[PDB]
Amino acid sequence: GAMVLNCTSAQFKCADGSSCINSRYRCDGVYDCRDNSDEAGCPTRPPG
Ligand SMILES: [Ca+2]
Image 1 (cartoon, rainbow, N blue to C red):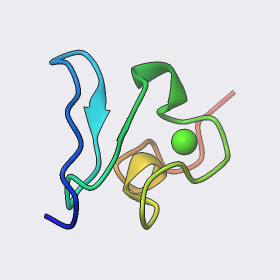
Image 2 (image 1 turned 30 degrees about the vertical axis):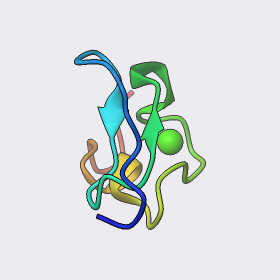
Image 3 (image 1 turned 180 degrees about the horizontal axis):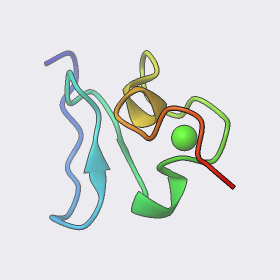
């Protein structure tokens, strides 16, 4: 919990909680979290 950021229930909190990003920034290609938990907890190579 290194500098826990405050977000809503809709927004995605990082694994450590150090940052919050949008739910629209879950699964896009880039890494928005402190590590990469935003795309780690995401479908592994989406079919289509
Ligand atoms: Ca992302």
